Image 1 (cartoon, each protein chain N blue to C red):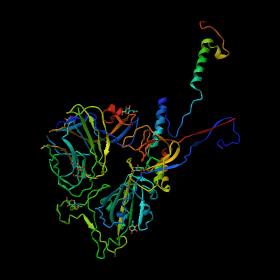
Image 2 (image 1 turned 120 degrees about the vertical axis):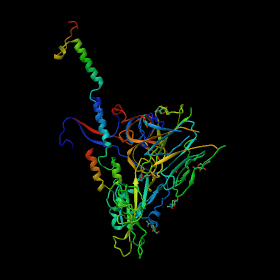
Image 3 (image 1 turned 180 degrees about the vertical axis):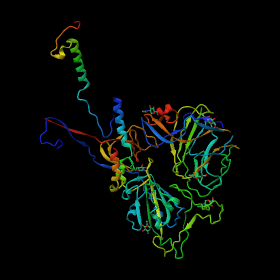
Image 4 (image 1 turned 45 degrees about the vertical axis):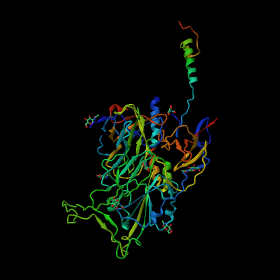
Length: 49
Length: 230
Length: 300
Length: 50
Ligand SMILES: *[C@@H]1O[C@H](CO)[C@@H](O)[C@H](O)[C@H]1NC(C)=O
Ligand SMILES: *[C@@H]1O[C@H](CO)[C@@H](O)[C@H](O)[C@H]1NC(C)=O
Ligand SMILES: *[C@@H]1O[C@H](CO)[C@@H](O)[C@H](O)[C@H]1NC(C)=O
Ligand SMILES: *[C@@H]1O[C@H](CO)[C@@H](O)[C@H](O)[C@H]1NC(C)=O
Ligand SMILES: *[C@@H]1O[C@H](CO)[C@@H](O)[C@H](O)[C@H]1NC(C)=O
Ligand SMILES: *[C@@H]1O[C@H](CO)[C@@H](O)[C@H](O)[C@H]1NC(C)=O
Ligand SMILES: *[C@@H]1O[C@H](CO)[C@@H](O)[C@H](O)[C@H]1NC(C)=O
C-alpha cells in the first residue's frame, strides 16, 4: 500500500530475477536431460528418444 | 400544479474540508433524485419553508432580484430580508412589516412598511453583476443559515437541463430565528419568469472527488436497489 | 538484552525502533489585537430574569481568561468539556454568553443533562455541552429590605424545553379542562411566580448571579483565543507545529494542490490531516510524517 | 489473494478513525483539552478498541 503511519512492508529475499533464473535452469534441465538430473548428475540425450 | 422532474440536481459540499481522489459517504439534508419540483411564473403565492428549500431561476430572468423569509407579516417576530440592487445586496434582519405584493420609465423599491428592534445591518458584496442559469440552496440548523449557489450558462429556457452541479458555501449567519414560510421578490417598471422550488429530506449520499478536489459524480443510497449495491 | 541470554548464535534479530526527533517548535496565530468586552459581562449591572435570559454573541477578539482563574469573588467555578487551565492556548470559533439570576439552592440543577424545575422548564443544558458556567452570591445588590419582586420564573407547562430556547409569553395555564380564559380559577394557575428576596432570608434563599459560557469546535476558521505569541515558520525538517489548536509533529513542505477559498485543511485518506492553510501567507503546506523505522542487528 | 490482503489492511487503517465512546477520536485533542487525572479515563477506552 501507500505510505502512511504505523506499518511498513518488507521486500522478499529472492527477487524476480532469481526466480526467473531458477525456472530457466529447470526448463533447460528438463529439455536436455529428462528425469535423470532430478535423481543425480544430468545425462545428455536427444529429445526424440 | 405543473410539477416537474428534478433530474439529479442539488448537491453541495457538506464539510468544508478538502478531499481529493476518494469516494466518501455522507448523511445530511438533500434533495432526493428524480423528485417533483414545483413550477411557478405572473404570480408569486406564499409557500412554507419545510426544513429546507431548493431554488432556481432560468436565464435572462432579470425580473427576480431578491427573496424574503419570515413567519408572520404583522411584525410580531423576527424576519429576514435579502434585496439585490445595482451596487450591493441589502441583507437586513429586523422586525419589519412588509407590503403583501411589492415590486423592485424605470421604477424603484416599494417594500418596507415599518421597522423596530434591528440586529444585523452589514452591506455585503453583490452576488451577481444562451445565457446563465441560477441555483440556490437554503437550510436552517442550530440557528445557522447556510447559503449555497453556483451560476452557469445553459441554452434552454423553460426546462431544467441535465448534467451535474455542486454548490459552494458562499455566506453564513447566526440569525437564530424560527422560519416557517417565505416569498420571492420581482421587479417591475412603471413580465412572467420561471422559478422552481424543491424540498429537502435527510438521506445518505455517496460523493466522488476528482483529482482537483471538486465534485464530479454522486449516487443516492436509497433510490434504486442497484444504487444500494453501489 | 532482548533475547535474555549472555551468548547469542549467528543470525539477524530485530531489536527496537527509532524516530527522528523534532528540533524546534513553531506556533502560528492570526495577528489580531482588539480585546472583546468581558467588562460588561461580569461587571455589568443590568441583568434579566430566569426565563428572560440574556443572549450575547462575542467574537473577533483575543481573550485572557487569567481574570477568571484568580478572581476570588467568583464563588463556584466548574468547567466540564475542557480543563479550566487549558483555555489559555486553545483556539475557538465563537463563544456564547448567557446571563440570568437564580436562587442559590437551584445551582446544582444547572448541569449537563440534569433534571429540575429550572432545568426542565426554564433553561436546560445539553448532554454534550462543551463550555463552562460561573456563579457567585449577589444578596448585597439584588435584595431590598422591603423585598425585591422584579425577578420571575415560569414553572407550569406541559413538555420539556429544548436546550437552546427562550419563552416570555405568560398565557394562563390550563391545568384542567375549564377554559377560564385569563382568569385564575381553581382549575387554572398563572404560569409565573416571583422570588421574595430579602436580606433576612437564609443563604440558600439569597439570590445568586449566574453566567454561562459555551464553546464549539467546528471546521470553520477560529476567531477568538488567547494571547499566545506566534513565531516564524521553518520548512524541510522535522519540527513541532501549532496551528490554531491543531498540534502535531511533521515536516512542512510546499504544495501543488489547490485549495478552494473556503477550505482550510485536508483529510484526504482515513481522516488524516495532510495539508494546512497558512493563516498569514494563505499558502497550503503539506504535512509529512517524521521519519521512522525498525532496527536489525547482524551478528556472527 | 492480493485483494483480500489489501482490503484487510485498508480496514485496519480505517479503524483508527473510530471514536469508541470517547469525546474525540484524536488523542492529541484529548491530551490538549483535558487535565490528565480525568483524561486517562478517556485514553483507556481508545486503547482497548485499538
Ligand atoms: C408529482 O406529484 C403528482 C401529484 O401531485 C404526481 O402525480 C406525480 O407522479 C409526481 N411526480 C413524480 C415524478 O412522481
Ligand atoms: C443598495 O443597497 C445598499 C444596502 O445593501 C445601500 O447601501 C445602497 O445605497 C443601495 N443602492 C441603491 C442604488 O439603491
Ligand atoms: C420591539 O418592537 C415593538 C414594536 O415593533 C416594541 O413594542 C417593543 O418594545 C420592541 N422591543 C423592545 C425590547 O424594545
Ligand atoms: C416556530 O413557529 C411555529 C409557528 O409559526 C411553531 O409551531 C413552532 O413551535 C416554532 N418553533 C420551532 C422550533 O419550529
Ligand atoms: C484541474 O482543472 C483544470 C481546469 O481548471 C484542468 O485543466 C486540469 O486538467 C484539472 N486537473 C489538474 C490536475 O490540474
Ligand atoms: C498580519 O501581518 C501581515 C504583515 O505584517 C499583514 O499583511 C496582514 O494583513 C496581517 N493580518 C491581518 C489579519 O491583518
Ligand atoms: C470590575 O471593576 C473593578 C473596579 O475597577 C475591577 O477591579 C475589576 O477587575 C473589574 N472586573 C471584575 C470581573 O470584577
